[PDB]
Image: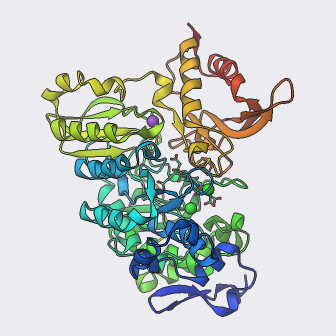
Amino acid sequence: VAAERLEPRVEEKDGYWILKEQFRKGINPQEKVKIEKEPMKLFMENGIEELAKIPIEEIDQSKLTKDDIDVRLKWLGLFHRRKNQYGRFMMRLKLPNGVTTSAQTRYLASVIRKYGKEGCADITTRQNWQIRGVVLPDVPEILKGLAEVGLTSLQSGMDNVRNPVGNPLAGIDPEEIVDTRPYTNLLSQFITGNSRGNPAVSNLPRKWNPCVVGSHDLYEHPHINDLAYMPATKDGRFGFNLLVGGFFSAKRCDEAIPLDAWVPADDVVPVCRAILEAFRDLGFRGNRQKCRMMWLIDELGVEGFRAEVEKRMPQQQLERASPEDLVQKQWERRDYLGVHPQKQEGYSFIGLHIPVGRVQADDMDELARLADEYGSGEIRLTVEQNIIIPNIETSKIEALLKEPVLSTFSPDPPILMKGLVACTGNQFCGQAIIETKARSLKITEEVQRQVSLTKPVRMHWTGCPNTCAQVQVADIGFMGCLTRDKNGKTVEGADVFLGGRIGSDSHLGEVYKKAVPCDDLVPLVVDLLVNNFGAVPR
Ligand code: SRM
Ligand code: SF4
Ligand SMILES: [Cl-]
Ligand SMILES: [Cl-]
Ligand SMILES: [K+]
């Protein structure tokens, strides 16, 4: 690869990072949006204050302001639901390691409550909160309210570093490798500039997903992250081996590969910065389907990319990977739902099933109440869109199990529900081909009525090829499509995926059967479970 290819393509100008004039040819429309006006100015220069005052019908009359609300606002975690909930915004947080408080939960509930039938909230596949129903005029007050309770929504969408995922059992599991919270906290603080905004990492060629591993279970899905920190001792020192470039897209799904790099634990932020700077400086900015970091790694080769990371490290030092990491390959992924003892004697955590991750304001208040009465006011989110309430004095468990709300958010739902994951789908998402959340619950309920089983089969439902619900990791995955019934009528369907494995022995699933009408999935799935997963007809 020629030396000219390694010239940084962006430069700092007045606090922000912009494409250099000579690298602007052939760029995609999103890159043009970023050049036309720096999205971070909406927050960092309080551009949102005046924008929020303009009636949305007027906003839609000019490209600049329409791009503000449809594109640039995603840098403030605000997502206009133009097609399916016009004039309303989904709002997405930074929530490193999935950790929330009862006060934060009540605040979020109070926001969605205002919007009535237009409001609700969702736990995401990055153990994060999304709230719904937000109107533009309310945005300045919501931003203030979030800050007041110690939350940020910065840089959660578009060409930004996404929610830092960690071990949902961090600090509490007797079997953890290393508490991931300090590291995911540091990453989030770095990414968001301590909630003020960090323009140095907000003009990436594309989204970028990080995780820090602290579990033998690999709850963090390191194989599908742009950067995964794998805990590893090297030459008597604790640190992390680095995996890079994992991603899913409509066009291509790839597992992360070794960078062949180990960093001491204190270098977590420095190496995150170095990798992001290399991606920012050198990444392709044409066809959006070829802008994820793995495409850069393929273009330079992993060694060429590694050299770019190395030159951006303090003292330009980057050690090679440790021959072994601390993750034990002899491991069975553990169920976290139900009551489990913590490493702190006399304390338990409880995992509660949240059906397809969907909650209303009243539900959130009740969960916050439980966390206060039984725990320490902490609620943890998981990437299967469930919750854990930690730090419960074990003597309180008997009373907790009798709480009425646990009939809805159960510590021991049927096994197929335990593993069920579903994206937003067409209730709110404009890209969705099908409805996902209600359908997946209905189908799963019918399937489980017909068969019993003991294997923890994981079913993932995603509404379009963006695969936000990660169908390629599922035992049985369902990707939304339109198909045809026996009479040739248009019906909702799914492409069915098999072969996904998680944990250390990970594998990406692939399409098994295309174009199955959703109304025909129950018998197909029942038979798959009996024939391949040991299920028994009732
Ligand atoms: C909420 C969530 C799914 C869920 O129900 O949990 C979600 C929802 C959306 N995703 Fe995603 N993605 C979610 C995790 C993912 C993941 C899974 C992951 O991170 O492990 C992926 C696949 C992994 C990956 O990115 O490598 C994913 C791949 C995408 C893509 C395809 C990326 C690509 O390279 O092509 C898009 C479209 C895009 O970015 O161009 C997308 C775009 C979208 C948008 C923002 C599209 C839009 O604006 O409507 C969706 C918002 C719908 C809504 O109203 O909720 N989403 N999205 C997840 C939020 C995570 C978070 O808290 O930050
Ligand atoms: S997979 Fe498609 S339908 Fe589901 S949330 Fe992502 S973009 Fe929307
Ligand atoms: Cl986005
Ligand atoms: Cl839309
Ligand atoms: K769930």
| Residue found at x 18% / y 41% | 372
- Height in image: 175 above or below 272? above
Viewed as shown, does residue 400 lie left or right of 326? left
What is the count of numbered marks? 0
| Residue found at x 59% / y 37% | 436
Quarter where residue 240 is shown:
bottom left
Among all residues in the image, which is located at the extreme right?
A: 488
- Height in image: 290 above or below 84? below
Q: Point out the quarter of the image occupied by ligand 5.
A: top left
- Give x and y (percent) for residue 290: 71, 66
| Residue found at x 64% / y 65% | 294
Q: Nearer the viewer, residue 302 or 226?
A: 226
Residue 38 appears in the picture as rendered: yes
| Residue found at x 22% / y 36% | 370
Residue 507 appears in the picture as rendered: no
Quarter the N terminus occupies: bottom right
Quarter the C terminus occupies: top right
Q: Nearer the viewer, residue 231 or 468?
A: 468
- Give x and y (percent) for residue 289: 71, 63
- Give x and y (percent) for residue 344: 17, 40
The figure's colour scheme reads rainbow
Q: Nearer the viewer, residue 457 or 25?
A: 25
- Height in image: 191 above or below 475? below
- Give x and y (percent) for residue 142: 34, 62
Viewed as shown, does residue 389 lie left or right of 430? left
